[PDB]
Image (cartoon, rainbow, N blue to C red):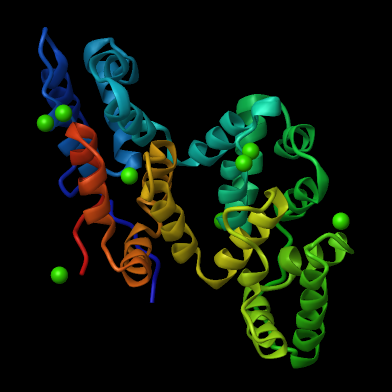
Length: 319
Ligand SMILES: [Ca+2]
Ligand SMILES: [Ca+2]
Ligand SMILES: [Ca+2]
Ligand SMILES: [Ca+2]
Ligand SMILES: [Ca+2]
Ligand SMILES: [Ca+2]
Ligand SMILES: [Ca+2]
Ligand SMILES: [Ca+2]
């Protein structure tokens, strides 16, 4: 009855002993990667920040700098991601994704569609503090169309609270969405954006069900997951997140590994960002929906200490 992650506070935690263990693992010409990944994946993010502070006090060195030169490749990328303070991680990923014409719309869509209003408010505040501009202004400057407008509405974090069901508004909203999809999501965009973006979660779940009976198909089937523009991808992310954030993020992990290549950036981002929120539930949806465990997919597709660390973050195999 609760959302659970795969990383919890290490019991008996001693930040000074852990700092000593990490320094021992790097001091000298060699490296003890196993010690580094076992400790860091078994301490919570808050504990990692206390280790980093004890490390600087004990040794007069910067733990993150040492990790960056001591480790390489995807393993370094994963460890560095785990060290970023949780409160800063989403804001950082958004800022990194906003790069003019090379902007990574997949990341904007993933984070903004799946974070709660409480999470989005924290993100916007943190983002201004770190980067000196508003998240909205950067998003508007680097996106276009009704995709831009939908992100802006979602960024407003003004979604109705879960309240008494109104079957009259359900039917009206479902009809409005059916008509909007019949026009390929290219007409009266402001009207369906208000529905997807500001109605309550429980309300929209009923709307989607009413859409089924009205239309004969599920609302997702109006959008081709592979051959759709940015707005359509966002609507799909919002619909899926309304149904289940763990299921949306599980599907995101699934497509990150399926096919040729591995989208390691997405693999790292989802595992780390969700490790203390809902990664256990993500695993459950992953196994239920894709007939195989997240553990087995990571194991088959990745290598070395990066794989070892990802498997420890995953926590367990599922079947
Ligand atoms: Ca090792
Ligand atoms: Ca893009
Ligand atoms: Ca894109
Ligand atoms: Ca909150
Ligand atoms: Ca149009
Ligand atoms: Ca793969
Ligand atoms: Ca290796
Ligand atoms: Ca089993």
